[PDB]
Image: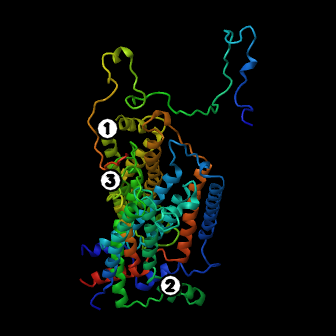
Amino acid sequence: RVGNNVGFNAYRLRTSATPWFGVGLEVAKVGENYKLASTQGHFLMEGRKKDLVRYGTLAEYVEDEKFLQVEKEEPISLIGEYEYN
Amino acid sequence: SAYGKMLEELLGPKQTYESVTRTIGDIVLTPIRKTPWGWPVGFVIAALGLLMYLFSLAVLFTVGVGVWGINIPVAWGFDIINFVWWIGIGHAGTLISAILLLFRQDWRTSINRAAEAMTIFAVACAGIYPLVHTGRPWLDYWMLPYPGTLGMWPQFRSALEWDVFAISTYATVSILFWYLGLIPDLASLRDRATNIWVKRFYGFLALGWRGGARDWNRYEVASLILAGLSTPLVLSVHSIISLDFAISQLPGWHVTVFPPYFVAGAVYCGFAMVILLLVPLRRWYKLHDLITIKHFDLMGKVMLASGLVVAYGYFAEIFYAWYSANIYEYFLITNRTMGPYAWSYWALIVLNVAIPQLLWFKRFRVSLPWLFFISICINIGMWFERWVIIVLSLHRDFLPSSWGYYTPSVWDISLYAGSFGWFFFLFFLFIRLLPAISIFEVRDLVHKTETEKALA
Amino acid sequence: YRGTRLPWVIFGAGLLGASGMFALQTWINLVEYPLNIGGRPLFSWPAFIPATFEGMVLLSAFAA
């Protein structure tokens, strides 16, 4: 009841002489607006770097250790804080 | 006189205290099997809206809160866009009832009961939505400060707990300032009954009033205090229904001019509903001599004077979204003007700050086929403001990997389109059983026109 | 009639709703069940005012 008719069976295209890749494919679009239940919404970092994945290379890390860190001032909070001891 | 020519714009022809009481005591006391049409065909259209309301709720409890279409990015949808819309509608029903009574104004007099009752039924339609948008609606008593065998209380930092405290104060003093107004009025429907089973009905709703200066002085010092207590209430209620976005840290939600700009939009969308309801209460009930067109010339000016504060609100929150150097509020401007839901914000600038900017001219204020199209573009448009505030800030937010869409299902439409049933089920029960115009106050307005003509 | 003593009944119940709801949420958050909820302080003197104001309007109009 889980895996019945969820996708297309790719095993009907294996040919036992080209069982992993072959170059004789014809696409020939015959449909429109499938469901395709995806769970990400946006696969594109929208300038939200410094907040999602700070990416650098090792060439710039061996000269500066905290090159992806932002040495900024302590933020101000009006709620105070609690003591986790 | 400069003051007498103000009061003569509110009544018109020759009117006494009886001819005023007769034309309001003929909307009521016209018996069934003699009751004019329109009210039967509307009360059975509202029944099909109420059976669309009670079926969408019986669905909602049984299968769940997730037949709506609310996603996990945007988890507040038509249950909250229509809730702030309905709460927004009843607020100018109490600007008419309470805020204008502070100003001793006499053009609020005939617009009173069609705005006191219009507040209540836009709260009874509203107040179901904070009780049914919860996924477990049978525990909404947990948002009440009661003692139990759990040591648990509500939070009292969330602005949805204050929504309990605002509406359950707004719902009870709307039905206490409209029932107090009906205490001296249902004593007049009692004495005009001449039928003891409808005389006992209005002789028990009105508790036994008699008039009397020792009761009339105690009435108005309990009315203007109530009109002085319902005026910081509704500037707070739709501010507290405004804090439950502005408490949240979201980029389109965490703006700090939300509390005066929502209540501006409440006395913008609300005056649009009083205009959308009273233009078909002159052509159908013959109230051309009580709801004279100066009342719409002044309801249009206050709707205009409220529609600029939200015209200020759209430009301030698009300025301080740019004036903040956030990438999340830079994106907020480029997600209302561009992006997938850009049509909603451009059907908002058109319907709120472009089309009802014809309200400056009297040509589109005295003309009721033009004031109706302007006010019908505010109820659709101020729904779209609360869609832009709620959905367009929720469906795209800080993290790009949580960007949703919220296309509503039929049970989001059928609950909203069914909610107009429960409004007009009770509004058509209000029109038939209760006076639509406060008779004793417009008797004072007839007395005020006579006492200023006698000063000559 | 020389007026009525009714506005002092409205104020006497408004001072009992304002000081009765502000002391309700303070007794909840400090004495009865103090909760680290959001890192916010126990005596949150903001966020008690939009709930002690609506208790001031409620008990005043219940005396009005």
Q: CA distance from mark 3 to mark 1?
A: 19 Å
Disc 2 or disc 1, which is closer to the eye?
1
State which mark lies toward you, 3 or 1: 1
Question: Marks 3 and 2, how far apart in space?
Answer: 41 Å
Asked if the residue at tag 2 contacts the one at tag 3, i.e. Cβ–Cβ closer than 8 Å, the answer is: no
User: Where's the C terminus of chain B, which quadrant?
Assistant: bottom left
**Chain containing mark 3:** B
Determine whether, in the image, residue B413 is placed left or right of residue B92.
right
Marks 3/1 same chain: yes
In percent of width and height, residue B6 lies at 30, 72
Residue labelled with disc 3: B309
Residue A46 visible to an observer of this rendering: yes
Looking at the image, residue B400 lies above or below residue B349: above
Q: Looking at this view, is B284 or B72 the one in front?
A: B72
Residue sitting at x 45%, y 42%: B392
Rendered residue at 32%/78% (across/down)? C12
Q: Is residue B295 visible?
A: no
Give the residue at x 62% y 70%.
B40
Q: Does B53 appear above or below A80?
A: below
Q: Please name whichever residue, A36 or C43, is drawn nearer the observer in this view of the structure.
A: C43
Q: Chain ID for label 2?
A: B
Q: Secondary structure at mark 2?
A: helix
Label of residue B189 in the image: 2
Q: Amino acid at mark 2?
A: Leu
Which dot marks residue A23? none
Amino acid type shown at disc 3? Val
Whichever of callouts 3 and 1 sits on the residue coming sooner in the sequence is 3
